[PDB]
Amino acid sequence: LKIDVKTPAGKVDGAIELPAELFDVPANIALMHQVVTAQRAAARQGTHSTKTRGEVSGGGRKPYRQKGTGRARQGSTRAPQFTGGGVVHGPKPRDYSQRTPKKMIAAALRGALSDRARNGRIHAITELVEGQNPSTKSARAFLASLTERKQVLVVIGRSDEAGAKSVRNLPGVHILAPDQLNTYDVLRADDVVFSVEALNAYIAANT
Amino acid sequence: ARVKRAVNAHKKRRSILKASRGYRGQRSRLYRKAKEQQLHSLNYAYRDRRARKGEFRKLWIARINAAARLNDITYNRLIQGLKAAGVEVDRKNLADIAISDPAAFTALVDVARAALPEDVNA
Amino acid sequence: KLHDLRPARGSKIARTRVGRGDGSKGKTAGRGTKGTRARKQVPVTFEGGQMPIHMRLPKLKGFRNRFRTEYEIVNVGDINRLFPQGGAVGVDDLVAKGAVRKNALVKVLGDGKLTAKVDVSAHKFSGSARAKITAAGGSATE
Amino acid sequence: PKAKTHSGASKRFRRTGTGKIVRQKANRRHLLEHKPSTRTRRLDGRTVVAANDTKRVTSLLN
RNA sequence: CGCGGCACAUCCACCUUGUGGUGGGUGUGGGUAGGGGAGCGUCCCUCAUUCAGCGAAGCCACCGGGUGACCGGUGGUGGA
RNA sequence: AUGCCGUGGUGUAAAGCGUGGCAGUGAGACGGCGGGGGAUAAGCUCCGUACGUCGAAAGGGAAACAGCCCAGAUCGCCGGC
RNA sequence: UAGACGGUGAGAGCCCGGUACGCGAAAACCCGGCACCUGCCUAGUAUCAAUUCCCGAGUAGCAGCGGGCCCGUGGAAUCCGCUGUGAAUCCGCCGGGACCACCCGGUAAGCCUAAAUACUCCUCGAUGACCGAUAGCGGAUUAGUACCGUGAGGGAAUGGUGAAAAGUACCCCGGGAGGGGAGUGAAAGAGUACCUGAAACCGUGUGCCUACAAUCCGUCAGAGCCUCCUUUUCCUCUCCGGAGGAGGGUGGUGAUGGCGUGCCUUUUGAAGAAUGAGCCUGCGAGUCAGGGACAUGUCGCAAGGUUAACCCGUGUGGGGUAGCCGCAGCGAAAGCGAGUCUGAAUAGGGCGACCCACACGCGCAUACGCGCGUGUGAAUAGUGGCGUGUUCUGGACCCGAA
């Protein structure tokens, strides 16, 4: 509710109290389930194509007449049951996205983050740079010296000087801007790291 | 997502065939012909175990009758007498006694004869 | 986390796959016949050949006025509980409270004892609404 | 892509403010000399749909 | 009828006493079309975890297990 | 005579009613009992029974036997009546 | 600022080609900029009397026959086309759903007009809860080929050695192919016909039954042998083994008895002499889009709910209030409202509002409740998404006609 981490290459600074949105929420696993599966549904490209009768070349001829041949009533040379035939009830290239209520999305997100606050997994850091240029090595020492976990979510913002360059090439580390803070990354990652600006922007947008 | 439905089917094929072993001709070689036989065989086992129980009663009765006739008494009056005596002894072990100890069978016959009343009137 | 994330109990009903053996649903599966229903769906309209109810019954009498300006209906009891202090009632205020459809003309019903002495800046009041408004001590407008 | 309402049903049935549908009776448009006022009063008015076809009618309207 | 093992309703006394379950009683359990309920299994994505060239998959034989769909172990072939 | 409607008790486990969801059936057969059609006919056809069985019911019996007699299989038992 | 993929003898950040990122175009092309060149104007703007002309002609409009617009000649406007006739230039003409007076609007029969929108032969870079050789385009391999057809047209099958060919030197049988021995090789149980190598099928060796005996070719009883094996008489050879055997128990075989009329479909009804299947492997038949509809279960909210298109951005999140359903319904409609309609009125009737174990103020009542308000804390609901079942239009469970 009211805790702050240390500062890189320093001592301690900040001390920002977290609002109720990140603590007083009874997160519901069914809600988070539905929202997460919506995200996985959106992640699909829907490229699963096939070929049905009519796209298969030819097949309009009706060989093997119905008298004096002793063969089955063929009727077409590209029917499903034939080698090289069409696919019946195939995976047509669907294009979909499980549209959900915005209140469900927000409630699930603040629920997950509030659970992280309950377990002390929020590391609202201040920055990560050697002044202006990136240093992945120093990023490794910082993140692996304060968090000591595999999967980490990093929220910086629109700062590309030492934002999504120092944290890159760190297996398990993903990065995003506050506006795109989804839930799947939050549930996958444990020690969720925020910048001061990440907290100000998130809180301001979310009252 | 093509799944290649071979494996799942093979579990059935190899199970049914390894159980069907010993059947003659196109019974222990062909899945679809073996399958028929397992249905008929197991329906047969289902009724045959029960019939077996009845059959064993028939055999036991025949043997008891044979020994009883050797002691000059019928099965009818033998069982009637044993019931009057309260000798709740099954036909399995009674038929066993007929072989293991014929003298004990004779003793049971004397008990039944004594227990029987007098005649066929009531 | 995701490995502890579960669906709600009672939801996620399994899809009853139809043509997958006799123990699952059946060979004919619902369509346990040989007639039309087995092969295709008969239109719900068709009764059999006799005149369906759609032609058997007479045509609904009358017509529909194209120039019918429908008014939204405001419950004076809702006014009573919504604005217990009165003061002033605007249409923008009522829709701001969500008591009536946006961008529409309104009418006032009298079903409910009105105690709030408040003038209503709106349209088309009923005679009983005037009875209740003047009972409270207000004034009707249009 | 989008449902259709049977136009005859929309022109013959009238839904009420609740879960009820009524049918206009009008077997009185051809010959009205032999029919008594008793019979024409039985036909006059509007009658709720009998419960023996509402599961069909509601799908016909919707 | 008797003696044991499964199951479905109802009931008795309980544990989170209509969510969900424990001990016990009674009755019930042939069944196609058809309704409903509860499950096994092949493949695939993801998360946690993990055996794995000191030998996986697939396949074969054997021995075992589950009320069933089916599952495991051992040994051999093979080599990711 | 049976049978039907209703009523007051006794008895009964779910059988009933209403409102909804989803289907099947919409070709029946035989026997017994009342009929009619027919020839005082038929393993003929058409009717009724809250009469049954098969259909959808294995088993025992009728030598063999879907419809007749007895009887409604949860599973096991080298136990009985 | 490189943990994207792939390759290399097996699963590689650090071995390699590469990626991140930064450089990089003589010449040509495209784009953009600059100069030249090209090209327009010695004003009609403003106030005014309103004598005169003009504002697109065989056109408009009319009539007839047709088309099409929700509009099926119908009361049938607007628009287009054909055929005859045939006006006017501002006090004008046409339209505003037959039509007419009034009113608002714009001035036809002449031309041009990029963006927003649609599409992908082809060429880039990337993706994939897409396929892995009977799938994917028909075509991974001499593929629109071989081949069929007068021809238009129709239209196949064949993938995999091993890390490296290191493709078995040499010898021996044999005419050769082929095989064996040697040898390379981790392995030939990877030899060009080859990764893994199932089944049908063929065949051999061997344990067991069978030539006086009928039965969906089984099941249950069930002797005797075979094989595995415990205890044991016993061999005393015992620091070994257990030989052969009684008895007991697995895995085979099975003498002989009992019982017993293939499977599926369709049928009032089947073992079938009703149909169908030669066998094995593989392929294959109730699925999906939609802010669809109905019902139901769970999950968000709570008289509200919810956003579609669309904008920003990097994963699909944040915004977007136009709209929808609900909220008050009745009536042909006007209309009015808890009433409303028919109706002279409704006394009645169609439709919808309002359920107490009960107190306080109040009329009635022996007791029990009718009614106006606050609660003794009295009775209640829709909307959206994901699922399930059904249903509608979509090839609609699949295959099949003439």
Image (cartoon, coloured by chain):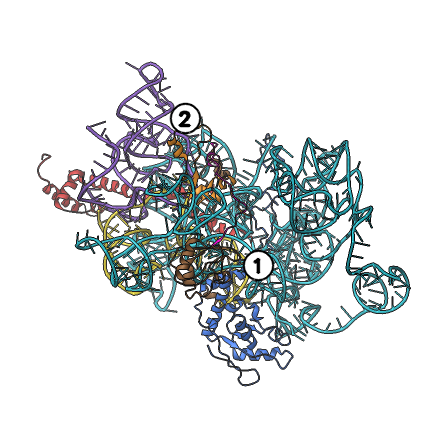
Chain colours: A blue, B red, C brown, D orange, E yellow, F purple, G cyan
What element does badge 2 sit on? loop
Q: Position of residue G317 (x, y in %)?
A: 55, 65
Give the answer, above or below, for where A46 lies relative to G147.
below
Is residue G393 left or right of G227 when viewed as pictured? right
Residue under circle 2? D34
Amino acid type, residue under disc 2 in the picture = His
Is A88 placed left or right of G387 in the picture?
right
Instruction: Judge whether residue A204 can be spotted in this image.
Output: yes
Secondary-structure class at tag 1: loop
Task: Tell me the mark number nearer the camera, choosing from 1 and 2.
Answer: 2
Residue G277, given in percent of the width and then of the height, sits at 52, 37
The amino acid pointed to by label 1 is Arg
Figure quadrant of residue A69: top right
Q: Is residue E41 left or right of residue G137?
A: left
Q: Which residue is mark 1?
A: A44
**Image coordinates for residue G295, horizontal then vertical, percent:** 42, 49
Extent of the magenta region: C49-72
Relative to the observer, which residue lies in front, A22 or G248? A22
